Amino acid sequence: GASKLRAVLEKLKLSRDIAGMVKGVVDHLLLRLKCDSAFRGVGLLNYEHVKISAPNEFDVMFKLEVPRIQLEEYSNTRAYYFVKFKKENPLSQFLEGEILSASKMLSKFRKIIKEEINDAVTLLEKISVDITLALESKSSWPASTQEGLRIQNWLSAKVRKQLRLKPFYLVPKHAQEETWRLSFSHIEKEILNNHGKSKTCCENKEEKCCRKDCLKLMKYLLEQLKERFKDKKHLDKFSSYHVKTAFFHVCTQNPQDSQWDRKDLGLCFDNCVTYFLQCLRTEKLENYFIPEFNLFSSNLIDKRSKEFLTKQIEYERNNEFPVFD
Amino acid sequence: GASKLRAVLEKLKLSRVKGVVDHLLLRLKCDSAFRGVGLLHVKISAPNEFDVMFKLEVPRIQLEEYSNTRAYYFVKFENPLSQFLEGEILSASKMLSKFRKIIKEEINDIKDVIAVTLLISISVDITLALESKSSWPASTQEGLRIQNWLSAKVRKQLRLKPFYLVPKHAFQEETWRLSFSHIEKEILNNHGKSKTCCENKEEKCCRKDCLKLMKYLLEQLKERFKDKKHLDKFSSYHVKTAFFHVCTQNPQDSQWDRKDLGLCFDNCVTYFLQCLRTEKLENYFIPEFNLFSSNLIDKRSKEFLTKQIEYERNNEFPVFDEF
Ligand SMILES: O=C(O)CCc1nn2c3ccccc3n(CC(=O)O)c2nc1=O
Ligand SMILES: O=C(O)CCc1nn2c3ccccc3n(CC(=O)O)c2nc1=O
Ligand SMILES: [Zn+2]
Ligand SMILES: [Zn+2]
């Protein structure tokens, strides 16, 4: 009974000329940001719609390369780090000790943005834009990612070796307000747009896979229930990031394109539901890149919250997903 | 059938200058005209001979095709190469002379070391190549037909990479010729339709070994008939070009199973022979350039190579063992 899923995927495409006009404003923001000494080498990372149900909301990431870093891990959190330096730092005014202050460099970031309005941050009638700034280190990835990104049986060890030569990024997130969180935003995009074991996956009629459709249906399912139960607040800590990482673990578990054939959209999606449910019950959802970081730990999400989402998802599947209508 | 063939590949594995190049890259970078200069085995039977190409990015180039040759171009344009201008043309004649001058005076500082060929105790051949980060020229539009093999997605990615121009006489002595040897390497080392080709026992393919055997067979015939000199104009580049066309014809990894090495190599030999007889071997990247036209290679030279190759294939390739 995948015809209901196929219909949903067609309506989600309906709500997709949606348009590129924040690329004007982001271009004008990027001009005066380079005029400052601290943000000279800042360029755009990639639109990127976090919410697949709100095409009128975008998200862009601004990257600034840092020349010389020695990273310092906060406690055993393995995802949050202190950024310490090894010429003349243009971010020397953001130094609180040996630690580049996240808060300091963010404050300057919003100031110049609030100075271009008269001509992290979210910008205004029916469109919004979420802006994030990230450090770029072209160095080797930290030791916590050594066992992550298990794509060797799927996209090959050769591709994993090439992806890990690319730079990694750090975004400002509290852990304590002096920490930076690892981010591989660029890698998840590259993998999803180059997702088959076959290099010609989805390029011909004989190799049509349903990986991308399963991810979309997964994100739509969570957003729909997040708005259905928007009052209880039990679902507020659940985001499409959790759904994406679970989908990537499923791709690792099912590496052949034979296991994602478009005919089997029903079972593929159902197996994506099931793995997500299993992570909820056992309270275990490892970061795809940082395998010892548990997104579904009791420290970050309450068990009662996961039990409510499990109950609702199981209800939806048992009744042919009325959430989609 | 692959018994003798695999025994030949096992010998070629057993048979497998850094400093000299590094000391040359520094004293060359000291010159203004060659400020941006960086790094980027031609023979399988001569492992005491290496091959290296030095790249130098030229910022903004305006190419002009020389008389519908599709491969040779004049390069027109704070310019560090204005010393080598002969009007508005970057004269390859003057560019390659200043190149040899710095090297010839630098191998004086290893005290015996004698485009340019170095002799050590071992031989190294150095080539100079301008790099343009622009889009590839129009003569290349229909080349690199890898869409059914390595995917159109990959073809557009490789097409975003820079191309290179090498000083080669066309004779007009200041023309530059297109070069994509960097693309050839990436295709050869990432060669399957499946990204895990040759990464497990289930997906073992015989593409790389098929090309090695074709290069070996050519290099051996060259040594065998080196006196008569009919085979001097042939080279590994012709063999590699025919191989890439066979990869385009046979895009599935199942048509290259390691079990079928005998059939695959015989098919690779057969297509190369077809290129010889019909005198047609398109450049893989510039399809309108025929490497086997009678302008470049004598037809009797191709008929001599055909006769020799056809004898070897009919007699289980005896030339693989004689030397
Ligand atoms: O991938 C990106 O760059 C942004 C998306 C994203 N990454 N991310 C984490 C990455 C590492 C560790 C914890 C992380 N958390 C914790 C959370 O879910 O709050 C988190 N949430 C996110 O939304
Ligand atoms: O750098 C590269 O592209 C590979 C090396 C290489 N390229 N190349 C040619 C490229 C275009 C036209 C003719 C070409 N010929 C033979 C010839 O001049 O007829 C040739 N021999 C070579 O060894
Ligand atoms: Zn696909
Ligand atoms: Zn292979």
Image (cartoon, coloured by chain):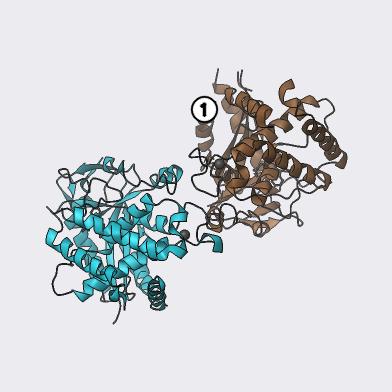
Chain colours: A cyan, B brown
Q: Is residue A197 left or right of residue A297?
A: right
Element carrying mark 1: helix
Q: The N terminus of chain A lies in which quarter of the figure?
A: bottom left
Q: Quadrant of residue B98?
A: top right
In what quadrant does ligand 2 lie? top right
Residue drawn 57% across the image and 40% down it: B205
Q: Position of residue B1 (x, y in %)?
A: 69, 32
Horizontal placement of A18 versus B119: left or right?
left
Image coordinates for residue A164, horizontal then vertical, percent: 38, 45
x%, y% of residue B53? 59, 38
| Left or right of residue B300, residue A185 in this image | left
A199 over B264 or under it: above or below: below
Regarding residue A40, the answer to whether it shows in the image is no
Q: Using the image as rendered, state which of residue A72 and residue A154 is in the foreground.
A: A154
Q: Decide which of A185, A151 is in the foreground and name it.
A: A151
Q: Quadrant of the C terminus of chain A?
A: bottom left
Chain letter for the residue marked with disc 1 in the picture: B
The residue positioned farthest toward the bottom in the image shown: A125
* Residue of label 1: B18
Q: Amino acid at mark 1?
A: Lys
